[PDB]
Structure formats: structure tokens, C-alpha cells
Amino acid sequence: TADAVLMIEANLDDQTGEGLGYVMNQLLTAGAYDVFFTPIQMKKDRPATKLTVLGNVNDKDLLTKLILQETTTIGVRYQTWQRTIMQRHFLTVATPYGDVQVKVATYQDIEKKMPEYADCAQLAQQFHIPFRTVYQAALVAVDQ
Amino acid sequence: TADAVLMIEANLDDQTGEGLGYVMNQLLTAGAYDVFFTPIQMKKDRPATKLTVLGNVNDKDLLTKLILQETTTIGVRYQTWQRTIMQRHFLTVATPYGDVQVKVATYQDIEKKMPEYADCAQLAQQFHIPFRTVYQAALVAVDQ
Amino acid sequence: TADAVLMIEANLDDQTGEGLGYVMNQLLTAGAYDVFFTPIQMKKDRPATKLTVLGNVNDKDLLTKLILQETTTIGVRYQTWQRTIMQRHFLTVATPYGDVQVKVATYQDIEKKMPEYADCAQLAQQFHIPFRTVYQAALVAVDQ
Amino acid sequence: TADAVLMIEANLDDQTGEGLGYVMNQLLTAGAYDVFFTPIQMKKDRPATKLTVLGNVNDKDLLTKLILQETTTIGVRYQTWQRTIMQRHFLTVATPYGDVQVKVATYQDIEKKMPEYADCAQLAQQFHIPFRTVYQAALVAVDQ
Amino acid sequence: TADAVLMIEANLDDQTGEGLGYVMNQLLTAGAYDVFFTPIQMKKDRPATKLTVLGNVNDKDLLTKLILQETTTIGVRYQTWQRTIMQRHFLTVATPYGDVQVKVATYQDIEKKMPEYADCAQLAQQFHIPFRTVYQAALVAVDQ
Amino acid sequence: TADAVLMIEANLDDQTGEGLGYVMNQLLTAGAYDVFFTPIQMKKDRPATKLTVLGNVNDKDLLTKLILQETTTIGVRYQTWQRTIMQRHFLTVATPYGDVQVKVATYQDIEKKMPEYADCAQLAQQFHIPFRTVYQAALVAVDQ
């Protein structure tokens, strides 16, 4: 399918990383689609960080306000981007360690399957096997 | 308030950092709002740098020409972004080390205060105390 | 001259670098103008990579499909950017090591010359001199 | 004072960030002093990640086996570094938003105070004030 | 087991990525165990690159002279690191797309299997299937 | 030749780039051989910076105390590295834009010449020509 997404950016040369991990969780809590950090270099020998937020266009006011309230930035910049998304569906698969949800993504003539992280990570911690072991066991089980 | 900003980008896989520090100062001298470096990885095992310039839209021709004249790039790409900016005002505050300008930023119902860097850095160098000491003394003094 | 370019982006927190070097060569093989990697930091302590592709706007469907087929991403985002490009021409120059193609770039009143990489690299490997030696010999020879 | 710390490194070009965020939690849980990710660029156009682990030098075997079991790497490299650490103790300080434990670090004639994050984050989420507001409120409060 | 590897580093702020990709190929050709690029930020607003070379400690002179001849740097620094490497051997495994050599690495009681990239890339380009498809097909196949 | 250099490192997740650019100027002023910033990713979703300082090994105390006084870090780690440095001397060379001091570096049978930046930058700003133009003009001029 197709949709649109707002991208909000901010350059922070006077902001600590501690506060940035806080703002990333606030934004995700607020419903941002995605949030990420880009290492950038700014004037006067400043190692800096660019904060990027992807979100719903109707959420523009909320995520702007969070950024302006929680970080040191005086302004933000935003742009709308177009999107092309694959259609999702999930299969639950039985492994020696429990059920594992596999996300099957399709688009036109593409079909691919991603074992979900939280499932694999929870079971590996429960039976103390490596995360790759649960992952591989999920692939093996989705063979049928 | 609200405004618009042009963003100009360039990928440089055949450009030294020495020349890049020169171009960043030329652009800031020319009135760029902001200029930053993003580390990027390009084809044929090239560690590269993306040069981003933010500027006034009527300055598009100048900053383009600077980039094309001073760097190795054959083309630049540019886009206009929308902005949401907080309203600024400054308070000058008295510290045991001298006056320090505090930038108070407001937007709707947000109010935050940033001690200015050059003020704090100049006074710390003058009295050889750590930059954090002048910073904290500025916060303390803006308490009233 | 002037033209427009599509920019396609994708954030990959569940993708290996091996597969990324493969997708970068597939995209360049498919006619992408440029492809690059940006190191980014995503949620849940994930060091991640942003994949950026620049391309012809009529190639949007191909490069999207490559990204969605070959990487783990569920969606891509794209935007059109405007371009300002210099006019190219090439001079072939004679060096003690052979002919070397120099790319001369002009725009309005700017004129700059870039010795081409593959030429210099091939000759340096053939006569085992440093790449800088062939480069400098090319500049010296384009003096006339 | 003087002390030592083991540094373990591993270059991972075939490892997802998802798995990397997982192994970072395993390593801290395993008693690593610190763990961090450095973006690096490896052969064959691979965007990659360097994993660095700091720990007690007697933990070489523990943290070695953890890295070899949970990540994809064939080998790790390790070296001992000397350390100089400040003395810590904590003060509870009264702020307009509540008490905050401030961390006081000393070394010879150096003394600096860092308000603790979790306290500040705790008060900020409880009173819907910005994290920067409480942090600064603590700094000002720690003046006496 | 236990072993040692020489690490050579050099900070390059006046070196293009083009030349860096070239020297990376020279170094691997010269018998370096590994080579990678780290983005770093140096004085005077310079976006720069750290070159790290791993090699046999008896190669100090070879790889030193290579770095000093082919790059722009005035000096390099080097240190010996200890290593812990897993035992490798290769299995050919039958997949729906063909045979794939899988790399089996062992250390004490740890055993993990990584399908090889070039085989997977070879089958993927031949049958126009995604690299992730063959890799997963190998993982599932290597279960027995 | 052979020599040694002290390397001091510190991981800073609660430190602004503003303060980092400041401490970089303090460190160079304090006689550090070199200082650079590496973007790193630390626990709890923190975009962070690694500070590396190179110096004389007898400066351990000077540069240690500087880092502990001016930055936020609780500890630093340090190690001695061996060095191999080329011999420098400077030539003044005649270019169409003026005389430029070129730096000639030697080691055994290796000889390379790097025109100096500040001279090139000086002539470029004076005659409004590109820095790449003067640099290349120097390279060509240094052929004899």
C-alpha cells in the first residue's frame, strides 16, 4: 500500500546523550513511527547528533512540541515524504522452545519472512540458548 | 513562529577533510544558517562525507556556487523544508565571574533557558575555572 | 544544468552488513545514480544503518522493489529533490605512465579539474607507484 | 588512583543491530564495566559495527565466551588498559520538584557533582516537566 | 586458544575516500588480517577517517611502509593485541537452490554455523532470488 | 624511527558537543599531540562521544586532570602505543598565486610532499580562488 509520513529533524550541538535517550522514549511513547540518531559534526569542533522522527502527519504538533520542550533546539524542520509499504501478515510457529511469531511481508511478487525479535529474545532468555538458536529454530519450523 | 528553509546536500567521496573545514567556514561566513558533516559510506570501499547546508531560500544560488566552486562535487541537490521555531529572548545575568547572557526560549507553553556558550567559555578562560562552573553559576544566577 | 532526482530511504535495524554490500551493488547495477550508508542508532540499543538511494524518478518502482526484495524493510520513503549540476567535459592527458582522463567541471564562472580515479589507480598498479604519484603527474600534465 | 580494565573488541559485518542490542544487554548483565558500539566500514562495501566491551581483566573468559556464543564473530581481540577513576559518593539534594540524589566525584583537588538521571527522569515523568528542567533545578540546588 | 595480532592506526584528515578505498585494497593484498575505517572528528572542523589495520606482528614493517607510502599520514601508531579465535572448517550443505559451503566455527563447547556469503550470492544472482532467501535456506538446511 | 605516545580515552554519554569542542581546545593548548572525537553508542539508547587524546607519556597527569576537570567523565583509561614517524622539513615553492611552504616528509626510501593548508587557505581567501586550485597549483609547482 501507499501513505505519507512526516519527517522532523533537529541538530543538537548543546545536548547530552542521557537527555536524548529520554526524548527518544518519550517520542516513541507518544506514537512516533520511528526515531533515530545520526552522528553529525557541527561548527566550532562540536560532535553533535541529528534527531530524526518519523510520524503521522496529524501528529506534527505533538512531536514538534516534545522536541522543543525536551531538547535544546530553537527550531525544528519538517517535510512530508511518500511511502511504499509491503502488506504484513503473521504466522505463529511451534519451536522446541515455544511458539514464535513470524512476520511474512509481501509486495507484488515479493514474499519474505522475519522471525520477530521479542519472541526469539524472550525464549532464548528463558532457556538460555543463544538468540540465533531460537531464530534458526523459527526459520526451520516455518519450513512447514 | 514559522518560516521555510532550503536544504542543500552533497556526497563527497573524493574530498579531503582539510578542504571541508575550509568550505564549512566559507559557508558560515556567507550566511548559511547551519552546516554539518554526516559520515557516510559510498561505493568502492570509500569512507565519505555528506555535506549539508541549511540556508535562506533566496541564498540558494550563493551557497550552491560555493559548494560547486570549493568542493569536488559535480551536482548538488536541494529541497525546501518547513520550520517551527520558538521565540527567543535574552536575559543578562550577573555571576561572580561577570555578566552572562541567558537565552530564554518559549513556544506556546514551553519556556527554557540556555546559558550562552561564548559567554561561559570566555569567562572560564579568563578565570581558568571549568566551563561547567561558569555554566552552573549562570543557572544559579538566573534563579532570580 | 538542472534536473530532479528521487531519494529513497530505509532504516535497517535487523539487517547484516554482508547483505547490505550485496544490495548496494544490486542497486548500482540497476542504474542508481548513487547509494550510500549512514550509521544511525535506533530503539532498543540497536546500531543500525540508513540506506539511501538516489535515482531517476522513472526508476522509482525498480529501486523500491529491489530494496523491499533484498532488505528486511517493510516500507520505504521517498522524496524528489531538485538538482543543480555542473557541465562536464573530459581531457585526456599524457603522463610518463600513460594517458589519464581529466574531468573538467564548469558552472557559470567555475572551472575545476578532477583526475579520474580508475585511470590513476590502474596505472599506479601497473607501475607500482603510489596513487598520489599518478594523480600529481596528471595535474602536472594538464598544466598544458 | 591506579587500576586496570580489560578491553575486548570484535568487528561484526554479518550481525544485525537487533542481535547487537541483545548482546549488549547480555554483556552488561554478565558484569561488563561498559559496552559500546562504534560504526565502522569493512571490506566489500560492508557497513559494520565494532563491539567494545570493558570489564575486569579476570573476566576475560566469561566475556570472551559470551561474545563468541551470542555474536557471529570468529575471533575477538583483547588488551589491558590502565585506569584513573574518581571517588564517588552520593548526596540527596532538595529541589522544587523533590529530592534528587546527586553524585559527587572527587580526584585529588577536583570535585564535580552530577545529578543522577533516573531520579531526574522519575520526577520529570511524574510532574510532566522537562528532564532538562529538573536537571538544571538540581544543579542550582546542589550549589549549597 | 591464544595468539597475537598487531594493530596499526593512522588518523587521516587530508585524505580522500577514493584514496582510502585504494589503500584498503593494497593492505588486504599485502596480507593484512583486516582493515576498517572509523569516522572521526579532528581539529579545525575536519571530518576525518581513522584507518585501522590488523596483521601479523612480524608485518609491522611491511604494513607500516605501505601506509606511509600510499596515504598522506606523517606517522602511524601500533600495538599488539591478544587474540582468541575459533576453529574453522567448512561443510557443503544441500539447499533447494544448490549446494552451499557452510562455515563451522568451534571454541571449547561453542559451535555455530555461518553459511558462506559468496556461495549464497552466487546462487542468488543465478536464480534471481533474494540473498536473504538463500541464506535462510542454508540455515534451515544446516540443521541436519 | 621508534618512539612512544600515550593514548587516553574517555566515554562521554552525558556531555554536550559544545563542551566537547571546548575541551578539545584546552587539550591541544595543554600540549596534546592530537585529539579526536569518535561517535559511539552506549547503554540506554545514548548517542555518545568517545574522546581520544594522544600525548607524551609523561603528560599522563596533566592530560588526565584536564579531562577529569573539564569533562563529565568519572574515569579515563590509558595505554602507551609505539610510533613510527616520518622526518619533516619545509620548502617554500613558487606558485602562480604566490609562495607556499610545502611540507616534505621522509622515512627510509619514502618521500612525499604535502603543501601546507594555511598558506593555501591564505592565498585562496586573498585572491578569491578555490582552495583546491591553490593546493593543486602547489602540487604541480612542487614537481621541481
Image (cartoon, coloured by chain):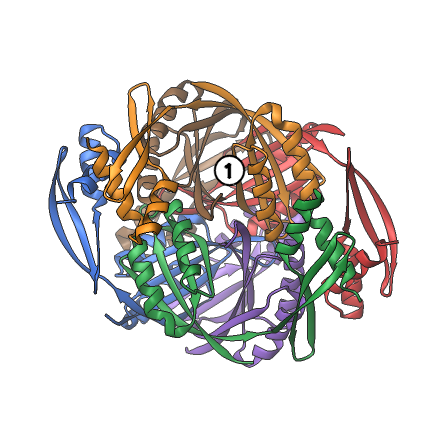
Chain colours: A red, B brown, C orange, D purple, E green, F blue
Q: Is residue F71 visible?
A: no
Q: Position of residue A25 (x, y in %)?
A: 65, 47
The residue at 40%/62% (across/down) is E30
On the question of residue E127 being in view, the answer is: yes
Q: Which residue is mark 1?
A: A73
Residue D48 vs residue B32, the one in the foreground? D48
The answer to whether B117 appears left or right of A90 in the picture is left
Q: Position of residue B42 (x, y in %)?
A: 48, 43
Give the residue at x 63% y 42%. Answer: C11
Image position, residue E36 (x, y; %):
46, 57
Nearest to the observer: residue D71 or residue B74: B74
Determine the image quadrant of residue B33: top left
Image quadrant assignment for residue F26 = bottom left
Residue A27 appears left or right of D79: right
Residues B125 and A39: in front is A39
Question: Label 1 sits on what residue type?
Answer: Thr
Q: Name the quadrant of the N terminus of chain F.
A: bottom left
Q: Residues within 10 Å of mark 1 (few under 14, many from 20)?
A: some
The image position of residue F55, as x and y in percent, is 30, 65
Could you say which is closer to the camera, residue C120 or residue A22?
C120
Seen at 56% across and 42% down, the residue is: C25
**Number of numbered markers:** 1
SS under mark 1: loop
Horizontal side, residue D16 vs residue A13: left or right:
right
Subunit ID for the residue under disc 1: A
B49 relative to A58, above or below: below
On the rendered image, what quadrant is the C terminus of chain F found in?
Answer: top left
